[PDB]
Amino acid sequence: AQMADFGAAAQYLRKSEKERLEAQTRPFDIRTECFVPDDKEEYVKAKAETENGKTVTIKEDQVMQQNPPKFDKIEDMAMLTFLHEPAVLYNLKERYAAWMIYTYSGLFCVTVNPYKWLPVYNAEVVAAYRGKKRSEAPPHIFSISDNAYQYMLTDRENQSILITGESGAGKTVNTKRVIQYFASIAAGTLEDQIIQANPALEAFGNAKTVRNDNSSRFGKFIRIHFGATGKLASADIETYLLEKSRVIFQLKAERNYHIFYQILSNKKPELLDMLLVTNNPYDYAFVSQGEVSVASIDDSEELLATDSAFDVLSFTAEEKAGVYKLTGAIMHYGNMKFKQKQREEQAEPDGTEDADKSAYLMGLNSADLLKGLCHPQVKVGNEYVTKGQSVQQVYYSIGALAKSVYEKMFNWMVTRINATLETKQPRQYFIGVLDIAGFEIFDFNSFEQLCINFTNEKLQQFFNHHMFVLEQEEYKKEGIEWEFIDFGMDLQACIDLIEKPMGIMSILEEECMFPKASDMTFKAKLYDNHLGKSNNFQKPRNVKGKQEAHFSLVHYAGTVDYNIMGWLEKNKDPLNETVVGLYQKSSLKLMATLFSTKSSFQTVSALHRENLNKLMTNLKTTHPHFVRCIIPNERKAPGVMDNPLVMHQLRCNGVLEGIRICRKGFPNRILYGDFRQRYRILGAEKLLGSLDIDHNQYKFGHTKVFFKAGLLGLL
Amino acid sequence: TTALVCDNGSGLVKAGFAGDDAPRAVFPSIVGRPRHQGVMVGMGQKDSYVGDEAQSKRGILTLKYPIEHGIITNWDDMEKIWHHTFYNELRVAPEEHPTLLTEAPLNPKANREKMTQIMFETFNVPAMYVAIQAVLSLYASGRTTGIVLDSGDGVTHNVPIYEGYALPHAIMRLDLAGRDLTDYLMKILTERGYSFVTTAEREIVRDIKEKLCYVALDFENEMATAASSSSLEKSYELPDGQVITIGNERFRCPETLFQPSFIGMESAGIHETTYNSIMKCDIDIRKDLYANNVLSGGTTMYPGIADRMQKEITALAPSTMKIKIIAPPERKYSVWIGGSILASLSTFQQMWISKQEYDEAGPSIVHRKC
Ligand SMILES: Nc1ncnc2c1ncn2[C@@H]1O[C@H](COP(=O)(O)OP(=O)(O)O)[C@@H](O)[C@H]1O
């Protein structure tokens, strides 16, 4: 009736009253149906003596009861009675079997990549979410989008859609479809415009990680603005913290950003003849520290797509040769060589060939570039004085210069994209779609993983505080007199040792400044300051046969083992202002554009923390809505999902964290009519005043009864 | 909140913010007062000019140094210089900034105690600290093992450090520096016809010394070569025209560092005090003290001082040790660079002398504990 107007999507949004009513009446026993752990499926159903094809006997306080058939396919997992990991996992799996790819978990809108075309977006018949609240329509992402729109027009606040970014595929189509729904409701199109500028940002911000083949190493915040009364306006994209330390150093089984190998694929001989570059990637130290080729993507067609995307933009013939020359110059930076002066400790160049090529590309003077790298000047008071630089310091300066040039070119490209997508009259509010890489638990974690996990700790604290506020409001509305400590800050604020000015990053910066520091001194300082005093910092359980870790943090998504070998070399970012002054006066117009705008202390961790503060400040002025896309399996098979994969994702996504949060208050919230009806079997206060069960496991207020997790499972 | 680094020095005040690469305010530590009459009514006469404002009105002022040999001898003048540094050069408010002062070793305790009392009483700084110039020079040199020869304008001293442990029984301090070389040059110039008696003329002599003087590798045959030809003659122009030409004074002035019997001192040269300070340490660390002779300060800037120091110490030390003289091109500001590095460290924010501790203890806290 109220659901039959979705057409061919009805079977994929809600099961008919027949199939639901016959699925809510299965005979299942209370004390002989539970979950037991496993090794390959990690969790299985069982009937202590248990059997599901094999027999196992485990402790009688590790079996969790299955939810009754009254909660078999619920579309809001905060309404189950037994909130544990197997329950949520198998509710996702069961809804994905009988195809229903979307499910709410408290505040999230969990999406599963179906790999199979479904008419769940098909016509306006399924775009008939226009006004239907979250509590009425089925669980679609359209409900998230339309409620963000309704909130924007009712409270006049900016809104944000924090979507999963760590997943391989299924996220880009979700962003495309959110933008398309926004274009459709408040109707060269905006969607096609945002999609046109994609290959450039891919070629310059996508890198082959080990657990991926096309990984977005930055945070893209697509903001689509709306008119005064709700008409769609232009859309600008805003990029956030970029993993710029990748331009220099790549781990094993990884690459840096694709543009290098794209140019170097010798698909267009004009570039390799103009850049004074060869075609062998093993000739340049900045591009061939990991691997130089992958078989999951061909580089020639990606290079054609990048060139054609540049041509689609307002890029002129000189503003493309400029970008290509700057990338070639960053390639030639890596293989400059300096030697210790004879009998002294000053660096002097041996071989000026790469210096010649880089200075001719960047439009500089080779002798001036070398003199500025070896003999930088400093302004002391009102005069100038030269400075000494060992070979290590000169290499640090070359690396920092390459990183700065690359990031400034990236920001310039984002600016030109924002320009070619900018046309409308003044506008009031917007809907942001934040896409950022998620939590990372590899077999070998390093500095970059620590930075990404810090960012995701911040985001999860943001979400937890948001849910704290909403729960406070929903308790005050129902008059439920029950106060509890803040969900967000008083739980994850302890794992932010990283930022407080004695934690991991502060100690790392101090070690970067201190003379003769090494990895062993850094490990010693970490242990002296944190081992035993803080309960989140712990020494790892190093097993003979696995990678050697040096410390372990208790994050929100488990405990991660970090390996500090090489953090001092990667955390240094000393900029040479003499070479920057040479840059500001370059003959190549694009370099002067990049560096148009009474220093030796710059580090990667400090810049990361500053950009993270900026991103969090942008987010905190909005009203967030969270989306969580999930990869069900690795072999693309639709319908079936692997439990270890999905459970790993469901831990890193933050869903199980929100469930742990909701499992502390009163998750099971039932109206008085439905409970007075279904559990009349012998107003509601009297009926509940006869059982032996308890008194504190429930709370009454204003036409709503509340229950703790596990009281509607006894009934 | 940032911290201030205010390396005092006896001839140049270098101030700035902890974390910067270089001091922002560098001006001569001088307080001058007008000697003459003053007849133009309404001119707007000032009581006394500090810093390099007294360097531009040098003609009518009498210049005074409130730091004689690393010891502050005029405290109101030092208060004037500190006030200038804080308000007119840095343009800050000291009540909002911890300040890291700096000092030479083996000087009276009253110096540190008065520094602390003046700061905490007349400037209301939240915290302060008084480091040693040599340790900061080592911080700035990028190493943890070495014997630093820090020679400024009031005092020359050696502080041998190994693996971050100072050997205080081997700290040697000597009381000739740039000012005594300036006086010896002023006295040695009169034998050519030029007479400088005024303090303004002392500053002129200082500039002559900074522009034309250099250290001779081998003093005797260099003196003979100067006596034979006139190829060591160079001309300097005083600030009224009236050029002067000097010959062997160029290398007779800085030779006083290695032959302090020129100015009637009984002590040894700087090379021999360095070697003695090395030979006062334990026999297991001098092999590494030999290869890390770190030079710092203004007086260590004469062209050819590194080669001469290395030749002397090599002639003194046994014929197996590798003598290395570390001479950075910016060694004039090593103390300040190291002070900013130290005040930037996170593990140091527990070492400040907080105003509350001062209120609890008294001015005697600065050396008894910190
Ligand atoms: N290029 C130079 N050659 C020789 N002496 C110099 C040179 N530059 C500065 N000086 C001397 O160094 C002194 C300043 O040294 P500095 O390290 O500032 O001492 P302080 O810290 O006590 O002021 C001045 O008196 C000056 O005579």
Image: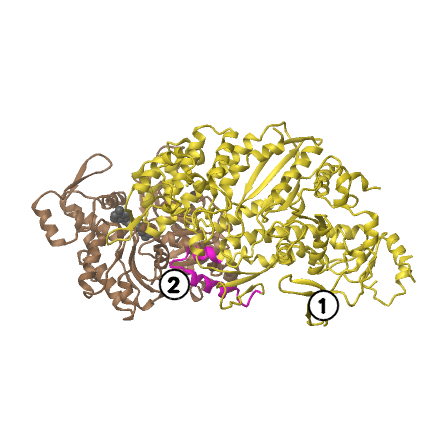
Chain colours: A yellow, B brown
Q: Residue at x 47, y 50 (%)?
A: A254
Left or right placement of residue B140 versus residue A608 in this view = left
Pick the residue in front: A685 or A559.
A559
Residue positioned most to the front: A53
Residue A510 part of the magenta-drawn span: yes
Magenta span covers which residues? A507-534
Residue A497, quarter of picture: bottom right
Pick the residue in front: A545 or B218.
A545
Res B109 label: 2
Given the image, on which type of amino acid does mark 2 rest?
Lys
Q: Please tell me whether the stretch drawn in magenta is mainly helix, strand or loop.
A: helix
Q: Residue B277: horizontal and vertical position, in percent?
A: 27, 65
Q: Residue A456: horizontal and vertical position, in percent?
A: 59, 52
Q: Which element type, helix, strand or loop, lies under badge 1?
A: strand
Distance (Cα) linking label 2 and label 1 = 83 Å
Left or right placement of residue A489 versus residue A538 in this view = right
Q: Mark 1 sits on what residue?
A: A51
Residue A184 part of the magenta-drawn span: no
Please tell me whether residue B239 is drawn above or below residue A550 in the rendered image.
Answer: above
Q: Is residue A471 visible?
A: yes
Please tell me whether residue A620 is drawn above or below residue A446 in the rendered image.
Answer: above
